[PDB]
Length: 51
Length: 52
Length: 51
Image (cartoon, rainbow over all chains, first blue to last red; front, side, top):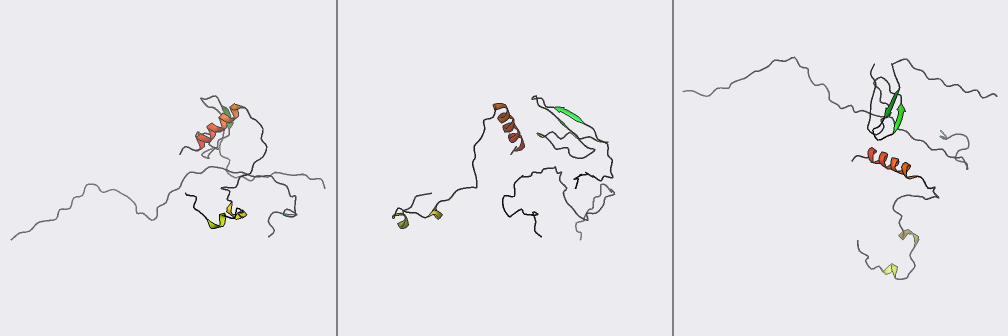
């Protein structure tokens, strides 16, 4: 004779946007170091990188 | 022959900056030059930055 | 873990490949430094490694 129903409840209708992509951008700093050496051989004749 | 050396540094931002003489509560006193929104070589966790 | 018996170790002469040095480290003569510099270095090291 009868059956149940299906209720739909709506609370808020806000203006949002879609999700095209997602990523995380972390904060970075400045770190560096070096070393001073002498030629003392044929490894540093003219330049450091040959080609 | 002479050996004159020039130092060029191009820049097209011209953001405001200042100097900061920070003194830690332990007793150490150091100085550094912060920029407008740019990290300033954080020393022992402190990352005080300047905004323009 | 255990020092198991080996037939090759009975002759008493072991080749050089059986000697391992964990890590690459070299030494040199040093100079004594005051305690304040060492304390500051230890503080900076323990501050840069909070984990």
